[PDB]
Amino acid sequence: QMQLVQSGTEVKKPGESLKISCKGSGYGFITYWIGWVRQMPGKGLEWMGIIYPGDSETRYSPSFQGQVTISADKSINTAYLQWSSLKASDTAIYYCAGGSGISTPMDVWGQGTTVTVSSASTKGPSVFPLAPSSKSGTAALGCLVKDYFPEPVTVSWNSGALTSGVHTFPAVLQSSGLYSLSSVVTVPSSSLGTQTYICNVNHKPSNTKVDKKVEPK
Amino acid sequence: EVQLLESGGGLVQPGGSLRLSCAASGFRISDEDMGWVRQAPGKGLEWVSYIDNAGASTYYADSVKGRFTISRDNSKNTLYLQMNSLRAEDTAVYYCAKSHYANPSFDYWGQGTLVTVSSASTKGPSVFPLAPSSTAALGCLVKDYFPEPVTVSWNSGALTSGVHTFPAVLQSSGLYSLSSVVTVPSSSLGTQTYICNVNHKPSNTKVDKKVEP
Amino acid sequence: DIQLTQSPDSLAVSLGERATINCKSSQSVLYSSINKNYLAWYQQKPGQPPKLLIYWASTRESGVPDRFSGSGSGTDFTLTISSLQAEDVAVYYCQQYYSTPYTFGQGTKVEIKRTVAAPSVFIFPPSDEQLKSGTASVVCLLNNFYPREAKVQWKVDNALQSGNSQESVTEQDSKDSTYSLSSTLTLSKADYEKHKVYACEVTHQGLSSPVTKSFNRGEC
Amino acid sequence: DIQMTQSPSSLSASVGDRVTITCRASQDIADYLNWYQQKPGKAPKLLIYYASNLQSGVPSRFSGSGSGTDFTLTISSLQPEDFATYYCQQGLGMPITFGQGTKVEIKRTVAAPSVFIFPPSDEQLKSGTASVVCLLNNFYPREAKVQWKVDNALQSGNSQESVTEQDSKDSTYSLSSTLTLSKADYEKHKVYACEVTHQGLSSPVTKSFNRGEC
Amino acid sequence: TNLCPFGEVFNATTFASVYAWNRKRISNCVADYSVLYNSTSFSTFKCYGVSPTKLNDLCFTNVYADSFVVRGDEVRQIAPGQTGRIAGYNYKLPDDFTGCVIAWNSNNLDSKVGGNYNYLYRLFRKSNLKPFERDISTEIYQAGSTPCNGVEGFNCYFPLQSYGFHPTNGVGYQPYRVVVLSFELLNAPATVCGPKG
Ligand SMILES: *[C@@H]1O[C@H](CO[C@@H]2O[C@@H](C)[C@@H](O)[C@@H](O)[C@@H]2O)[C@@H](O[C@@H]2O[C@H](CO)[C@@H](O)[C@H](O)[C@H]2NC(C)=O)[C@H](O)[C@H]1NC(C)=O
Ligand SMILES: *[C@@H]1O[C@H](CO)[C@@H](O)[C@H](O)[C@H]1NC(C)=O
Ligand SMILES: [Cl-]
Ligand SMILES: [Cl-]
Ligand SMILES: [Cl-]
Ligand SMILES: [Cl-]
Ligand SMILES: [Cl-]
């Protein structure tokens, strides 16, 4: 068959240029047309354009013509999508997808390239406790992972020991340009006395690992 | 094997019409280019019409434009040439032919069919013996017929050695005349029987003639 | 350009029952040369590229289970899952490849249908450590509710808050088939210290009346 | 139109000789030139397509060459069966045009005609017309002279003749001359003679009959 | 069990001029299309309306194999919706074209020291061709207001012109051989298939 492999994650400042790639490997690549698809976070799929590497015939969607350049190196079976000056509104995940002809379904997809455009710089999160209320059959507590860039962070409770009732929520982009999320565990454990509840957060982009114990105030 | 069998020719009045057909076999009539080429008696080859294997584009010589129409019937695998407002100059043997290339190259030809345009009436031939006198020679005089052609065999097809069937000449009366001779051993005269088979299809006349000394 | 409209936007059906998604095109998508409609259906699960389910309106791609079927003609097309299984929870898109520019439908989210369940609401005041910075975050938590539709409102001294909170919802749990939401109210430390009663009001079908969880600034 | 001119118009050549026929086009037709052979009473047969390609079933004795405006057909070893008219035809485009043809006759030894005379049959005289038939059998070359004389009176204007095409085996010709008279004119005179002149004969040979013998 | 005669098309000794493009209708046979898309000898392989990787699973009522030679820069003209002297005057594909345009460089076969001038194209025509239409007419094209009456001269051009294929030509002016495969399904038994069809 055919496989498409895309380039890695990108984290860029506004105004910077960018070129992401997509490589084919398999039988009969000469028959293949490579198109680009944009998916903004929580949104659907937007077709951007398509190219035939054999002669570099390129067609753009009218929504995207003038905004990007789609190209291809036929000596390495690779198609490219590039901008000259990124905006924060270019933040999305971009898929390449192949079909063995024009007016053909997209039967092969790359794994996607995540592109984050932002004026923020790398910053590790600050972790704050979500202390359980003293009132409380079942109680609830958690950790607030605030002000970190870029994504992602990982959260574990008591070092992977507690997994039932855990809900780590999707991150949220704050108007500051920094991300924030919360992880919450429903411990019906009346306990709250040497029951031990610590959250471990890892922000690999900043080499930030932080443990914090969530105790009743 | 590819074969093209023609029919439809014959005598027609000046200004009359006639449709020639060319039944093909061994290929599909519309897969390859097809054409009609004609030959007036004793003259050269003149291309008349053509139809291609792409968008069924048709072509006609100026000498027949507006009067002839070439077409095909796929269900019958047959080619057709419809000829209207015929003139004397249209009298000719008409051939259908196939071209395997878009550049016209006729690799298969039909046997041909004779189209005669004249006001003259059809008449059957009178067959007389050309008796041998006393290697010898004897024949048959196929005289006063119209139109062409006639066919002459000898002894129902067995005798084909030393046989010369001469081309017909148009007489002053406007009727054709012809003779068919055969050379045979002189001693074989008394033992053998000699019969000339004259067939004139246009008038539907068949005459078997005994030629005896 | 050819436009595609899917209906419904969301769909919940029980395990083993039939799910039906519809796609309407602004123009026919039929090639007369071979008598085929140039419409495809893709499935996308979170964190993954789309996967081609059906092409030529009704042909299944290699290895696609028989539960999925494509139907329709002209400008009306339908994807049908004859009996949903847990691995079918996802967003399904139709797409026309009749001619460029290729266009997609808006997508249809398919979730498992469940009995209505009321959310367990909790309120969390800001930590004293965060208040040392100069910003305060109050967190409201709605735990294990179905359906997903739920409204939270922040009331600070009974004044409604607008534009200073953000929400986040989990994905449907693989076991309980419920959702969970967290809402964060972000205030400056000064504005936080100008008021007393902080309240989160939750409205949900599982609740007969909105449940308000609240605390008072500076009380044990 | 694209005019096609062949050269020569006719030619004689002995068995085994190499025969060269040329064809010129008034315009450049690249390699789109075809050669056909046509034998008496038969449809033309394709010998060469695309200037130099030999058709299936055609012997390699025939070959073709040329390009642009000038083309050549070659018969390497002329055989008696090759007696025919050979045509070129451009296939560059419409209208299709042929050359005027080149008549190829086989040169043979000089063969003198065998002369026979046939008096009118009785049936024809009953019909009221007399036809005397003189036969010149298996001669070469084609040029012959037939002279009808009735009571040693040189006839003129009352005779027709036709010649068979060259024989595909012995390369000879045959000629029939018919003298047509009214039945009355036939019963008037007595001596009917056919005088034949040919290169194979030392002197003209005469075949005669007296009206009403055996 | 009859193998489709695609080899006659792709491996022909000489190809047609584009104005007199060749066409062969193919049916009642089995074809292994992979022999085409598993190949490394083709320079372009642009399919429209059908996936070549799915042809081995499909049957059609007819497959048309057109073939001809053009120069390199004109290979892109062999496609639906193209404008130019090839698409307009020589070989035209319909908007709903369903097939594959497969082309390769043939400079070693069709060029010649001294120049190969045996490949021609139509340069002038009074109107554009319909899809899959051929024109082998050689009438004098009237370019201006003056009638021509079938003689070349001022504003009276012979409509056919030669490619000049010399081996030293730039790649855009070198000869390319082109095969066009069209697939059609009428209301008739579909008799040309892949092995799995
Ligand atoms: C067209 O021809 C190629 C190559 O022709 C080969 O060499 C010739 C001299 C002659 O001997 C042919 O019979 C040979 O096949 C064909 O490609 C080859 O196909 C065979 C069998 O599939 C394969 O083993 C070879 O590796 C191929 N060689 C290549 C690709 O260079 C091809 O199949 C022929 N037909 C078509 C439609 O392209
Ligand atoms: C094409 O290339 C390789 C060769 O084995 C293989 O993976 C594939 O099946 C081939 N297909 C054909 C039909 O040769
Ligand atoms: Cl027409
Ligand atoms: Cl000579
Ligand atoms: Cl144009
Ligand atoms: Cl030019
Ligand atoms: Cl037209």
Image (spheres, coloured by chain):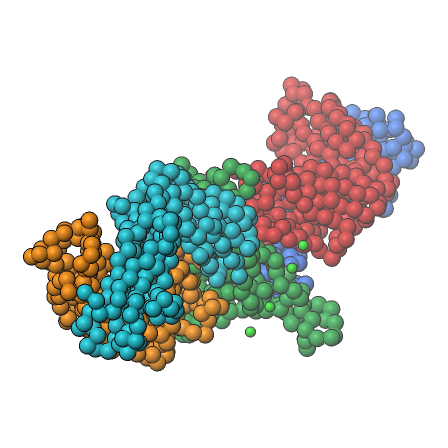
Chain colours: A orange, B red, C cyan, D blue, E green
Residue placed most toward the observer, D71 or E47: E47
Residue occupying image coordinates x 90% and y 35%: D182
Residue placed most toward the observer, E50 or E93: E50
In the rendered picture of this protein, how many numbered marks are placed on residues? 0
| Left or right position of A198 against A50 | left
| Quadrant housing residue C213 | bottom left
Residue D78 position in % (x across, y down) = 52, 50
| Left or right position of C132 against B155 | left
Residue D112 position in % (x across, y down) = 65, 43
Q: Quadrant of ligand 5?
A: bottom right
The quarter in which the C terminus of chain E is drawn is: top left
Residue C142 position in % (x across, y down) = 29, 56
The quarter in which the N terminus of chain E is drawn is: top left
Residue placed most toward the observer, B194 or A185: A185
Residue E22, placed above or below residue A59: above
Residue occupying image coordinates x 66% and y 58%: D95
Residue D59, placed above or below residue A70: above
Q: Residue furthest bottom?
A: A15
Residue C97 position in % (x across, y down) = 47, 55
